């Protein structure tokens, strides 16, 4: 037989990721402009001993071009992983979320939101498995793990947001070139 | 003392910083573990204008941190650290248009449909950028703008326009999940048929 | 006794009459002052099917009266007089599509935008035909159609769709200032993202 | 200097004609299905001594193709005339209109609606005067004049409608090819 349209699995994955991201983004924004002035931002960033995140060991691309030469499987392997990496860590952010003012910010609500999207991607990997040789290094790599507070937290918030954008961006690069007319005219 | 004014990325592919009025600027980006940061000077003080430095695609990367600073004789007038991804601010949509959607019989009222295109540099055809737009309109002789919720497509209707007056319309874009909104588009003046 | 069933003009350029089940038909059109009416038989009993006669562009004229009748042995089973212009009934619009217009946060509700194209035979690009369209939709497990006022463009939003259900959409055209409405388009099934 | 956009004169002429037509059409429809069955329709039509209208002496085209090779001026000369022809005759229909059930049906309301659109076209002739040699026969011809009741009336109604469609159709053929993007995509 041929193959069933994936435009429902994508619309359902792409909503979920877009949500995780919209959550990540707003909580960061909130935290940052209460306990982190430009002062602490640059210091933090200037010190990879704070600006560097655990999820930077699973090699992602860094610009349209390099990313637009990544086989579908590949892109979906990377996003599967970033999602898994944040599976435990989110545990922490918990209060921050359930202490924020975003309708939907909560440790649980997010964990489930991550376990949900996680299953969604594997499924597309099985189906939307677009040629791409399932034999490579990123394919052989498991996810990533995590080890004052104010900083520590804003550090995680920095990376959650950084990463959720990666995930949400890699999916759409798959969506557009797999479900025609979806990023239409 | 020249201080930074703005850094913006129109399509997440290249960026440029500008400042107020020799001032030179230096940059460094986290090339992996620690910074290579052999502080390099601006690679283009021309492409983008006066008091500007242009970073094309090859000096551009997303999700990798950047630090910048414009030095002077025995100086450092402004230090700046950011990351390209959080500095996007797409160009204004363009090619605005409108046409009657529903001829309102008696007159008085009328419904139209405004349309436009995404600015040309944003790769929305292949996924690099998703864009939300926002449109606003008002009768030409009033200063307050009627604001409309942000739609996700390049067309939408604006209902109940009183036919006995000229209106104006403008729209602006912003990549999803980023605070930016570039400039508004050129204004679109709306004059209706009226009287029949 | 074979009686006429229908005569329709899809684009005001050609027409065809059909009937129910040798029956032949004759025609005559007012070629100016009085009728030339040398009653000519159908010029095409094939192009349009069984029990049909096809009048292409060269046997077609607008605003000029036509008379028709399908004879039999010692017969005349149905006489018909009309005028092409008042017999238009354009084809169904086609290439239907939809996309989220506004992601409704919690779920429950959602807004979309349906789009389609004018059927291919209608010269709307140069003025021969102006078309109004009508769209209708309903949840797949209900028989009553939600009717929407006729819009003048090839796209429009349908708001408040409950996300927890599958809907269907169909549209149909009709040249302005003529009673016709051809058949509805192929149905468009709408399934939303839901849950997030 | 160059030239000012005509997209407002056209939107204003094209609304007016579309109205006259929508008026003409509906009153006909109404009259016809009260006092004229298929019986009388075919008889009437079969007899040009009833089916023929005065406004058929000013030579109009009769199919897309022939009409799409008519110079702008030309098309606008013909429509100017059909509008003028119906200037007096409408006098009659008066009751019919002010006896109908169409919000807008009335002798006066229509006369003015005809005098209005009439001025509108001449103006476009002056402006939208698109090359076209103002020297020809239709250009040298004035309009047309008019001489039981039930029939007489339905005869006029037949022609008003027939003609208002001609007018409204010839304008748009001018609109589209003169104001770009107006019959868009």
Image (cartoon, coloured by chain):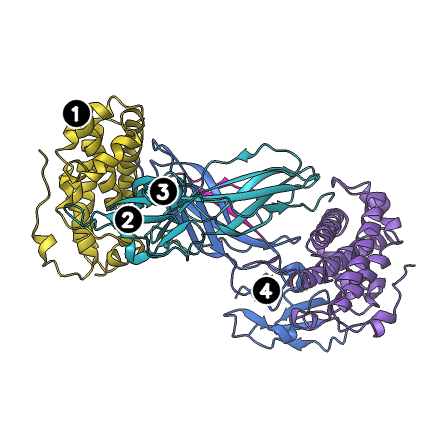
Chain colours: A purple, B blue, C cyan, D yellow
Q: Is residue A121 magenta?
A: no
Labels 3, 4: front one:
3
In the image, the segment drawn in magenta is B132-149
* C187 versus D116 height, above or below: below
* B46 versus C101 height, above or below: below
Looking at the image, which residue is at 23% across and 46% down? C64
| Crowd around label 1: few <14 · some 14–19 · many ≥20 (10 Å) | few
How far across and how far down the image is residue A123, in percent? 80, 57
Question: Label 4: chain?
Answer: B
Residue C27 got which mark? 2
From mark 4 to mark 2, how far is it between C-alphas? 59 Å
For the N terminus of chain B, give its image quadrant.
bottom right
From mark 3 to mark 1, how far is it between C-alphas? 30 Å
Mark 4 and mark 2 in contact? Answer it, CB < 8 Å.
no
How far across and how far down the image is residue D102, in percent? 31, 26
For the C terminus of chain B, give its image quadrant.
top left
**SS category of the residue bearing label 2:** strand
Mark 1 and mark 4 in contact? Answer it, CB < 8 Å.
no
Labels 3, 1: front one:
1
Q: Please name the residue that numbered disc 1 is placed on.
A: D149
């Amino acid at each position: 037989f041929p193959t069933i349209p994936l435009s429902r699995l994508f619309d359902n994955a792409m909503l979920r990721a877009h949500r995780l991201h919209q959550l990540a983004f707003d909580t960061y924004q909130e935290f940052e402009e209460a306990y982190i002035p430009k002062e602490q931002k640059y210091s933090f960033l200037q010190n990879p001993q704070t600006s560097l995140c655990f999820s930077e060991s699973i090699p992602t691309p860094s610009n349209r071009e390099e990313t637009q030469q990544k086989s579908n499987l590949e892109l979906l392997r990377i996003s599967l992983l970033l999602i898994q990496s944040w599976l435990e860590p989110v545990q922490f952010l918990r209060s921050v979320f359930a202490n924020s003012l975003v309708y939907g910010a909560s440790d649980s609500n997010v964990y489930d939101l991550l376990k949900d999207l996680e299953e969604r991607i594997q499924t597309l990997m099985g189906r939307l498995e677009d040629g791409s040789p399932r034999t490579g290094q990123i394919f052989k790599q498991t996810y990533s793990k995590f080890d004052d507070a104010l900083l520590k937290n804003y550090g995680l918030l920095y990376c959650f947001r950084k990463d959720m954008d990666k995930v949400e961006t890699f999916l759409r690069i798959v969506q557009c070139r797999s479900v025609e007319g979806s990023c239409g005219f | 003392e020249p201080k930074f004014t703005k850094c913006r990325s129109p399509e997440r592919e290249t960026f440029s910083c500008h400042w107020t009025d020799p001032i030179q600027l230096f940059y460094t980006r986290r090339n992996t573990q620690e910074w290579t940061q052999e502080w390099k000077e601006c690679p283009d003080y021309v492409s983008a204008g006066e008091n500007s430095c242009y970073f094309n695609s090859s000096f551009t990367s997303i999700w990798i941190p950047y630090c910048i600073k414009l030095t002077s004789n025995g100086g450092t007038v402004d230090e700046k650290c950011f990351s390209v991804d959080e500095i996007v601010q797409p160009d204004p949509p363009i090619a605005l248009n409108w046409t009657l959607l529903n001829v309102s019989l008696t007159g008085i009222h009328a419904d139209i449909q405004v349309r436009w295109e995404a600015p040309r540099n944003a790769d929305i055809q292949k996924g690099w950028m998703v864009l939300e737009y926002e449109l606003q309109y008002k009768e030409v002789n009033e200063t307050k703008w009627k604001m409309m919720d942000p739609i996700l497509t390049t067309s939408v209707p604006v209902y109940s326009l009183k036919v006995d007056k000229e209106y104006e319309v403008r729209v602006r874009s912003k990549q999803r999940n980023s605070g930016n909104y570039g400039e508004f588009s050129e204004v679109l003046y709306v004059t209706l048929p009226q009287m029949s």
